[PDB]
Length: 97
Length: 85
Image (cartoon, rainbow over all chains, first blue to last red; front, side, top):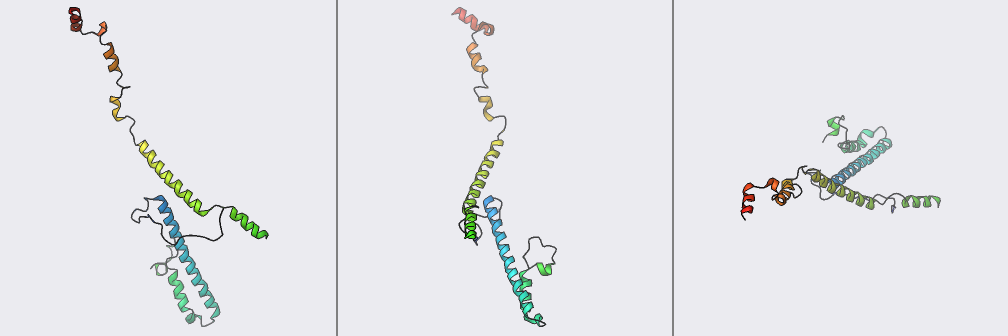
């Protein structure tokens, strides 16, 4: 049975994983894939937090929202640069570094 | 307290993540070892290397060495000499 209801993962790539030959070790391959998934989800959640603070900036600031939330707009648009897994239809001006 | 009991029961259910990961690693390693073993098992040819040297396959030699003195297959000079001595 599970001990407590809060997730315990490690924020470090699994050892004995060779980038040159990632398919040599199956366990290392699968753990590295899981770690990459976790990192991508962390980036996605960071972008979501930036988006939430941007929307609340736009709500709090009224007509003068173009200059008060400009920094938040730029931050969100640079944060959504490499979020996706298969978002290749998005233009490189907004989805490529 | 009903919700607390339900949460405790659910936690008593499910599986320990540490044990799940350990079992997963052990199973994957075992499968990899056994599959390379089965591949090397299949790699062997049907005809063995030493089959011409095997005692079971070289069964005529012993019998014919045993039976070489039978008159039906004797060398004539051997019979001549055994008659002479």
